[PDB]
Image 1 (cartoon, rainbow, N blue to C red):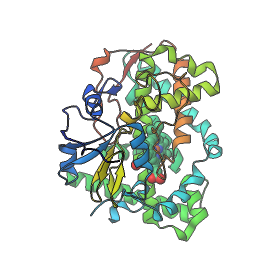
Image 2: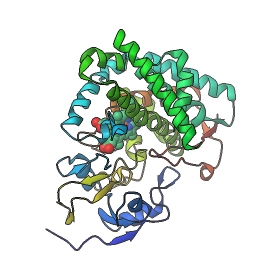
Image 3: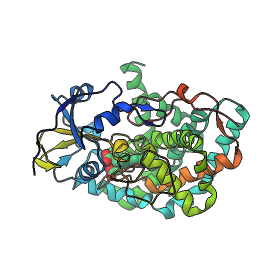
Image 4: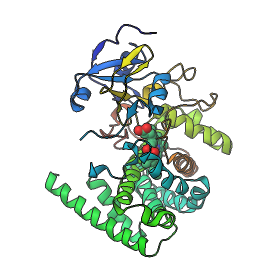
Length: 391
Ligand code: HEM
Protein backbone atom coordinates (compact mmCIF):
# COMPACT_ATOMS: atom_id res chain seq x y z
CA UNK A 1 0.00 0.00 0.00
CA UNK A 2 2.00 2.96 -1.37
CA UNK A 3 0.91 6.58 -1.44
CA UNK A 4 2.17 9.67 -3.25
CA UNK A 5 5.58 10.66 -1.88
CA UNK A 6 5.35 12.81 1.25
CA UNK A 7 5.84 16.45 0.08
CA UNK A 8 9.07 18.34 0.78
CA UNK A 9 8.30 20.95 3.42
CA UNK A 10 10.56 23.84 4.37
CA UNK A 11 11.63 23.53 8.00
CA UNK A 12 9.33 25.94 9.93
CA UNK A 13 10.80 28.95 11.73
CA UNK A 14 9.89 27.47 15.12
CA UNK A 15 10.68 23.87 14.27
CA UNK A 16 11.24 22.01 17.57
CA UNK A 17 10.74 25.14 19.63
CA UNK A 18 8.13 25.53 22.33
CA UNK A 19 5.40 27.86 23.50
CA UNK A 20 5.51 27.61 27.24
CA UNK A 21 5.61 23.82 27.86
CA UNK A 22 3.98 22.91 24.53
CA UNK A 23 5.26 22.43 20.98
CA UNK A 24 5.10 25.79 19.16
CA UNK A 25 2.09 25.95 16.79
CA UNK A 26 4.52 25.58 13.85
CA UNK A 27 5.03 21.94 14.86
CA UNK A 28 1.30 21.22 14.87
CA UNK A 29 1.12 22.73 11.35
CA UNK A 30 3.84 20.38 10.18
CA UNK A 31 2.06 17.44 11.84
CA UNK A 32 -1.12 18.36 10.00
CA UNK A 33 0.63 17.25 6.79
CA UNK A 34 0.72 13.59 7.92
CA UNK A 35 2.54 11.10 10.27
CA UNK A 36 5.63 11.12 8.05
CA UNK A 37 6.91 14.21 6.20
CA UNK A 38 10.11 15.29 4.50
CA UNK A 39 11.76 18.48 5.61
CA UNK A 40 14.50 20.64 4.11
CA UNK A 41 16.42 23.11 6.23
CA UNK A 42 19.01 23.29 8.98
CA UNK A 43 18.32 19.64 9.94
CA UNK A 44 19.05 18.16 6.50
CA UNK A 45 22.13 20.37 6.03
CA UNK A 46 23.57 19.36 9.37
CA UNK A 47 23.19 15.70 8.32
CA UNK A 48 24.62 16.23 4.81
CA UNK A 49 21.37 15.41 2.97
CA UNK A 50 19.03 17.07 0.50
CA UNK A 51 16.19 16.37 2.95
CA UNK A 52 15.41 14.26 6.06
CA UNK A 53 12.24 12.38 6.99
CA UNK A 54 10.45 13.40 10.20
CA UNK A 55 8.23 10.79 11.84
CA UNK A 56 5.91 12.67 14.19
CA UNK A 57 2.73 10.57 14.51
CA UNK A 58 2.62 8.14 17.48
CA UNK A 59 2.45 4.87 15.58
CA UNK A 60 5.26 5.67 13.14
CA UNK A 61 7.59 7.04 15.84
CA UNK A 62 7.10 4.01 18.05
CA UNK A 63 7.78 1.71 15.06
CA UNK A 64 10.93 3.42 13.87
CA UNK A 65 12.43 3.97 17.33
CA UNK A 66 12.12 0.22 17.98
CA UNK A 67 13.26 -0.93 14.49
CA UNK A 68 16.95 -2.02 14.65
CA UNK A 69 16.58 -4.20 11.54
CA UNK A 70 16.25 -1.31 9.10
CA UNK A 71 17.98 1.45 11.03
CA UNK A 72 21.30 2.19 12.73
CA UNK A 73 22.27 4.99 15.18
CA UNK A 74 25.99 4.54 14.55
CA UNK A 75 27.77 7.80 13.59
CA UNK A 76 29.03 7.91 10.01
CA UNK A 77 32.69 8.91 10.04
CA UNK A 78 34.91 6.59 15.82
CA UNK A 79 36.99 6.22 19.01
CA UNK A 80 35.24 9.26 20.42
CA UNK A 81 32.06 7.15 20.51
CA UNK A 82 33.44 4.04 22.30
CA UNK A 83 31.02 3.17 25.10
CA UNK A 84 28.30 5.62 23.86
CA UNK A 85 25.61 2.97 24.11
CA UNK A 86 22.83 4.94 22.36
CA UNK A 87 24.94 4.90 19.16
CA UNK A 88 25.54 1.12 19.16
CA UNK A 89 23.41 -1.49 17.28
CA UNK A 90 23.15 -5.17 18.26
CA UNK A 91 25.24 -7.20 18.91
CA UNK A 92 27.61 -4.61 20.41
CA UNK A 93 24.71 -2.67 21.99
CA UNK A 94 23.46 -5.79 23.72
CA UNK A 95 26.78 -6.33 25.47
CA UNK A 96 26.98 -2.78 26.86
CA UNK A 97 23.29 -2.76 27.77
CA UNK A 98 23.68 -5.94 29.83
CA UNK A 99 26.50 -4.31 31.82
CA UNK A 100 24.20 -1.39 32.76
CA UNK A 101 20.95 -3.20 33.57
CA UNK A 102 22.11 -4.58 36.96
CA UNK A 103 22.79 -1.10 38.34
CA UNK A 104 19.42 0.37 37.43
CA UNK A 105 17.01 -2.04 39.09
CA UNK A 106 14.36 -0.73 41.48
CA UNK A 107 16.20 -2.60 44.27
CA UNK A 108 19.32 -0.54 43.65
CA UNK A 109 17.30 2.65 43.22
CA UNK A 110 15.49 2.25 46.55
CA UNK A 111 18.84 1.94 48.33
CA UNK A 112 19.75 5.19 46.69
CA UNK A 113 16.66 7.10 47.82
CA UNK A 114 17.98 8.31 51.19
CA UNK A 115 20.88 10.03 49.53
CA UNK A 116 18.53 11.46 46.86
CA UNK A 117 16.04 12.67 49.49
CA UNK A 118 18.88 14.32 51.36
CA UNK A 119 20.15 16.03 48.18
CA UNK A 120 16.61 17.32 47.38
CA UNK A 121 16.20 18.60 50.98
CA UNK A 122 19.53 20.44 50.86
CA UNK A 123 18.72 22.15 47.61
CA UNK A 124 15.25 23.18 48.82
CA UNK A 125 16.94 24.69 51.95
CA UNK A 126 18.89 26.88 49.55
CA UNK A 127 15.76 27.78 47.59
CA UNK A 128 14.19 28.79 50.91
CA UNK A 129 17.28 30.83 51.92
CA UNK A 130 17.20 32.74 48.64
CA UNK A 131 13.56 33.66 49.20
CA UNK A 132 11.09 35.19 46.64
CA UNK A 133 12.22 35.12 43.01
CA UNK A 134 14.67 32.24 43.74
CA UNK A 135 15.68 30.47 40.49
CA UNK A 136 14.23 26.98 40.88
CA UNK A 137 16.05 25.79 37.76
CA UNK A 138 19.54 26.86 38.84
CA UNK A 139 19.17 26.21 42.57
CA UNK A 140 17.10 23.02 42.59
CA UNK A 141 16.53 21.28 39.24
CA UNK A 142 20.04 21.57 37.78
CA UNK A 143 22.01 20.56 40.88
CA UNK A 144 19.59 17.70 41.63
CA UNK A 145 20.17 16.28 38.14
CA UNK A 146 23.94 16.82 38.36
CA UNK A 147 24.47 15.58 41.89
CA UNK A 148 22.16 12.61 41.45
CA UNK A 149 24.45 11.51 38.60
CA UNK A 150 27.50 12.04 40.81
CA UNK A 151 25.93 9.73 43.43
CA UNK A 152 25.09 7.09 40.86
CA UNK A 153 28.64 6.97 39.47
CA UNK A 154 30.17 7.10 42.94
CA UNK A 155 31.96 10.45 42.70
CA UNK A 156 33.56 11.32 46.08
CA UNK A 157 31.43 13.91 47.89
CA UNK A 158 34.33 16.33 48.11
CA UNK A 159 34.94 16.08 44.35
CA UNK A 160 31.30 16.62 43.27
CA UNK A 161 31.42 20.42 43.44
CA UNK A 162 34.30 20.49 40.94
CA UNK A 163 32.95 17.54 38.95
CA UNK A 164 29.54 19.24 38.43
CA UNK A 165 31.42 22.40 37.41
CA UNK A 166 33.31 20.32 34.79
CA UNK A 167 29.99 18.80 33.67
CA UNK A 168 28.70 22.29 32.92
CA UNK A 169 31.89 23.66 31.28
CA UNK A 170 32.13 21.14 28.42
CA UNK A 171 28.36 21.45 28.17
CA UNK A 172 34.82 29.27 25.33
CA UNK A 173 36.98 28.29 22.38
CA UNK A 174 38.17 24.89 21.18
CA UNK A 175 41.43 25.24 23.13
CA UNK A 176 39.61 25.79 26.43
CA UNK A 177 37.33 22.82 25.72
CA UNK A 178 40.38 20.67 24.93
CA UNK A 179 41.73 21.59 28.40
CA UNK A 180 38.46 20.78 30.17
CA UNK A 181 38.37 17.46 28.29
CA UNK A 182 41.96 16.59 29.17
CA UNK A 183 41.25 17.33 32.84
CA UNK A 184 38.00 15.37 32.87
CA UNK A 185 39.70 12.37 31.24
CA UNK A 186 42.60 12.51 33.71
CA UNK A 187 40.05 12.53 36.53
CA UNK A 188 38.19 9.50 35.15
CA UNK A 189 41.44 7.55 34.66
CA UNK A 190 42.37 8.11 38.32
CA UNK A 191 38.82 7.20 39.39
CA UNK A 192 38.86 3.98 37.33
CA UNK A 193 42.32 2.98 38.61
CA UNK A 194 40.90 3.18 42.11
CA UNK A 195 37.87 1.06 41.20
CA UNK A 196 39.95 -1.56 39.33
CA UNK A 197 42.12 -1.76 42.46
CA UNK A 198 39.36 -2.21 45.02
CA UNK A 199 35.77 -2.20 43.57
CA UNK A 200 33.04 -0.66 45.72
CA UNK A 201 29.21 -0.87 45.39
CA UNK A 202 28.64 2.07 43.05
CA UNK A 203 27.73 1.72 39.42
CA UNK A 204 31.37 1.74 38.24
CA UNK A 205 32.52 -0.58 41.01
CA UNK A 206 29.72 -3.04 40.31
CA UNK A 207 30.58 -3.25 36.60
CA UNK A 208 34.28 -3.67 37.36
CA UNK A 209 33.30 -6.34 39.90
CA UNK A 210 31.01 -8.18 37.47
CA UNK A 211 33.02 -7.89 34.21
CA UNK A 212 36.54 -6.91 35.22
CA UNK A 213 38.91 -7.56 32.34
CA UNK A 214 35.98 -8.05 30.01
CA UNK A 215 35.30 -4.30 29.75
CA UNK A 216 37.89 -1.65 28.82
CA UNK A 217 38.59 1.67 30.56
CA UNK A 218 37.75 3.36 27.26
CA UNK A 219 34.32 1.73 27.40
CA UNK A 220 33.82 2.61 31.04
CA UNK A 221 34.66 6.27 30.42
CA UNK A 222 32.37 6.29 27.42
CA UNK A 223 29.63 4.75 29.54
CA UNK A 224 30.17 7.47 32.17
CA UNK A 225 29.76 10.09 29.49
CA UNK A 226 26.60 8.40 28.13
CA UNK A 227 25.00 8.45 31.62
CA UNK A 228 25.97 12.07 32.20
CA UNK A 229 24.59 13.13 28.81
CA UNK A 230 21.52 10.96 29.24
CA UNK A 231 20.63 11.76 32.82
CA UNK A 232 21.67 15.19 34.01
CA UNK A 233 19.80 17.56 31.67
CA UNK A 234 16.83 15.22 31.28
CA UNK A 235 16.19 15.09 35.01
CA UNK A 236 16.83 18.84 35.31
CA UNK A 237 14.44 19.46 32.39
CA UNK A 238 11.74 17.24 33.87
CA UNK A 239 11.96 19.04 37.20
CA UNK A 240 11.85 22.54 35.64
CA UNK A 241 9.17 21.81 33.01
CA UNK A 242 7.27 19.66 35.44
CA UNK A 243 7.07 22.52 37.93
CA UNK A 244 5.92 24.92 35.19
CA UNK A 245 3.34 22.44 33.96
CA UNK A 246 1.94 21.62 37.42
CA UNK A 247 1.75 25.36 38.29
CA UNK A 248 -0.26 25.87 35.08
CA UNK A 249 -2.56 22.86 35.91
CA UNK A 250 -2.80 23.20 39.73
CA UNK A 251 -5.56 20.65 40.03
CA UNK A 252 -2.88 18.03 39.16
CA UNK A 253 -0.77 18.88 42.21
CA UNK A 254 -3.17 17.17 44.61
CA UNK A 255 -2.95 13.94 42.60
CA UNK A 256 0.72 13.81 43.55
CA UNK A 257 -0.39 13.24 47.18
CA UNK A 258 -3.50 11.11 46.58
CA UNK A 259 -1.64 7.76 46.72
CA UNK A 260 1.67 6.14 45.68
CA UNK A 261 -0.11 4.77 42.60
CA UNK A 262 -1.61 8.12 41.58
CA UNK A 263 1.76 9.91 42.18
CA UNK A 264 3.47 7.49 39.77
CA UNK A 265 0.74 8.33 37.18
CA UNK A 266 1.38 12.06 37.60
CA UNK A 267 5.08 11.52 36.94
CA UNK A 268 4.42 9.37 33.83
CA UNK A 269 1.83 11.82 32.52
CA UNK A 270 4.33 14.69 32.91
CA UNK A 271 6.95 12.70 30.96
CA UNK A 272 4.40 12.06 28.18
CA UNK A 273 3.16 15.66 28.05
CA UNK A 274 6.60 17.24 28.34
CA UNK A 275 8.96 14.83 26.52
CA UNK A 276 12.21 16.83 27.16
CA UNK A 277 14.09 14.42 24.89
CA UNK A 278 12.01 15.82 22.07
CA UNK A 279 14.08 14.28 19.33
CA UNK A 280 16.54 11.45 20.08
CA UNK A 281 19.37 10.32 17.80
CA UNK A 282 18.39 10.47 14.12
CA UNK A 283 17.75 7.02 12.65
CA UNK A 284 19.79 6.22 9.52
CA UNK A 285 18.20 3.68 7.18
CA UNK A 286 20.56 0.79 6.30
CA UNK A 287 17.90 -1.22 4.35
CA UNK A 288 15.00 0.09 2.25
CA UNK A 289 11.70 -0.12 4.19
CA UNK A 290 8.05 0.72 3.57
CA UNK A 291 6.49 2.63 6.44
CA UNK A 292 2.94 3.98 6.41
CA UNK A 293 2.83 4.26 2.59
CA UNK A 294 6.28 5.83 2.22
CA UNK A 295 9.44 4.18 0.98
CA UNK A 296 12.34 5.10 3.25
CA UNK A 297 15.55 4.42 1.35
CA UNK A 298 18.80 3.04 2.74
CA UNK A 299 20.93 6.16 3.32
CA UNK A 300 17.97 8.35 4.32
CA UNK A 301 17.82 9.79 7.84
CA UNK A 302 14.59 9.85 9.89
CA UNK A 303 14.15 12.28 12.79
CA UNK A 304 11.68 10.89 15.34
CA UNK A 305 9.68 13.49 17.27
CA UNK A 306 8.88 11.92 20.68
CA UNK A 307 7.23 15.20 21.74
CA UNK A 308 4.79 15.33 18.78
CA UNK A 309 4.22 11.53 18.87
CA UNK A 310 3.06 11.87 22.51
CA UNK A 311 0.56 14.59 21.53
CA UNK A 312 -1.16 12.33 18.99
CA UNK A 313 -4.88 11.75 19.32
CA UNK A 314 -3.97 8.19 18.19
CA UNK A 315 -2.35 7.66 21.60
CA UNK A 316 -4.86 9.16 23.96
CA UNK A 317 -7.99 11.46 23.94
CA UNK A 318 -7.28 15.16 24.65
CA UNK A 319 -3.53 14.56 24.40
CA UNK A 320 -2.74 18.28 24.75
CA UNK A 321 -4.21 18.48 28.25
CA UNK A 322 -2.10 17.48 31.28
CA UNK A 323 -4.30 14.87 33.04
CA UNK A 324 -2.89 12.14 35.21
CA UNK A 325 -6.39 10.71 35.54
CA UNK A 326 -6.40 9.55 31.88
CA UNK A 327 -6.07 5.79 31.33
CA UNK A 328 -2.35 4.91 31.30
CA UNK A 329 -0.97 4.42 27.77
CA UNK A 330 2.27 3.31 26.12
CA UNK A 331 3.74 6.74 25.43
CA UNK A 332 7.25 7.03 23.94
CA UNK A 333 8.64 9.59 26.41
CA UNK A 334 11.38 7.15 27.52
CA UNK A 335 11.74 5.76 24.01
CA UNK A 336 10.86 2.28 22.73
CA UNK A 337 12.84 -0.85 21.82
CA UNK A 338 16.47 -1.72 22.56
CA UNK A 339 17.44 1.87 23.47
CA UNK A 340 14.46 2.33 25.88
CA UNK A 341 15.76 4.62 28.68
CA UNK A 342 18.03 2.58 30.98
CA UNK A 343 17.42 5.26 33.60
CA UNK A 344 13.58 5.28 33.52
CA UNK A 345 13.02 3.68 36.92
CA UNK A 346 15.53 6.02 38.57
CA UNK A 347 14.02 9.08 36.86
CA UNK A 348 10.52 8.12 37.94
CA UNK A 349 11.67 7.72 41.54
CA UNK A 350 13.70 10.94 41.70
CA UNK A 351 10.99 12.98 40.02
CA UNK A 352 8.29 11.71 42.44
CA UNK A 353 10.47 12.69 45.40
CA UNK A 354 11.49 16.04 43.88
CA UNK A 355 7.88 17.16 43.21
CA UNK A 356 6.39 15.79 46.44
CA UNK A 357 9.07 17.29 48.71
CA UNK A 358 8.87 20.57 46.78
CA UNK A 359 5.10 21.04 47.35
CA UNK A 360 5.20 19.69 50.92
CA UNK A 361 7.71 22.43 51.74
CA UNK A 362 6.37 25.27 49.55
CA UNK A 363 2.68 24.52 49.28
CA UNK A 364 2.04 28.02 47.97
CA UNK A 365 4.64 27.74 45.21
CA UNK A 366 3.87 30.22 42.42
CA UNK A 367 5.77 31.29 39.30
CA UNK A 368 7.28 34.73 39.93
CA UNK A 369 7.24 35.95 36.34
CA UNK A 370 4.71 36.05 33.51
CA UNK A 371 4.65 32.67 31.79
CA UNK A 372 5.77 34.34 28.52
CA UNK A 373 8.98 35.62 30.12
CA UNK A 374 10.42 32.15 30.81
CA UNK A 375 13.23 31.29 28.41
CA UNK A 376 14.29 27.81 27.24
CA UNK A 377 17.69 26.22 26.59
CA UNK A 378 18.91 25.25 23.15
CA UNK A 379 20.53 21.83 23.47
CA UNK A 380 19.99 18.13 22.77
CA UNK A 381 17.56 17.99 25.70
CA UNK A 382 14.87 20.68 26.18
CA UNK A 383 15.00 22.47 29.52
CA UNK A 384 13.97 25.81 31.07
CA UNK A 385 16.84 28.28 31.50
CA UNK A 386 15.58 30.02 34.69
CA UNK A 387 12.34 29.41 36.61
CA UNK A 388 11.93 32.21 39.22
CA UNK A 389 9.45 31.26 41.94
CA UNK A 390 7.85 32.63 45.09
CA UNK A 391 5.56 31.09 47.71
C1 HEM B 1 12.75 11.59 32.68
C2 HEM B 1 14.08 11.69 32.44
C3 HEM B 1 14.53 11.06 31.22
C4 HEM B 1 13.94 11.00 29.96
C5 HEM B 1 12.59 11.66 29.52
C6 HEM B 1 14.83 10.17 29.19
C7 HEM B 1 14.60 9.74 27.86
C8 HEM B 1 15.33 8.83 27.11
C9 HEM B 1 14.95 8.44 25.74
C10 HEM B 1 13.94 9.23 24.89
C11 HEM B 1 15.83 7.52 25.35
C12 HEM B 1 15.79 6.82 23.98
C13 HEM B 1 16.92 7.38 23.13
C14 HEM B 1 16.95 6.79 21.72
O1 HEM B 1 16.10 5.91 21.45
O2 HEM B 1 17.83 7.21 20.92
C15 HEM B 1 16.72 7.28 26.49
C16 HEM B 1 17.87 6.49 26.51
C17 HEM B 1 18.84 6.47 27.50
N1 HEM B 1 18.78 7.24 28.67
FE1 HEM B 1 17.19 8.32 29.37
N2 HEM B 1 15.89 9.71 29.97
C18 HEM B 1 15.75 10.30 31.18
C19 HEM B 1 16.51 10.02 32.32
C20 HEM B 1 17.68 9.27 32.23
C21 HEM B 1 18.62 9.13 33.34
C22 HEM B 1 18.30 9.60 34.80
C23 HEM B 1 19.69 8.45 32.88
C24 HEM B 1 20.93 8.13 33.49
C25 HEM B 1 21.03 7.69 34.78
C26 HEM B 1 19.33 8.08 31.49
C27 HEM B 1 20.20 7.41 30.64
C28 HEM B 1 19.98 7.05 29.30
C29 HEM B 1 20.85 6.27 28.51
C30 HEM B 1 22.31 5.99 28.83
C31 HEM B 1 20.17 5.88 27.36
C32 HEM B 1 20.71 5.03 26.22
C33 HEM B 1 20.18 3.60 26.43
C34 HEM B 1 20.59 2.62 25.31
O3 HEM B 1 21.02 3.09 24.24
O4 HEM B 1 20.46 1.39 25.51
N3 HEM B 1 18.09 8.57 31.16
N4 HEM B 1 16.38 8.10 27.50
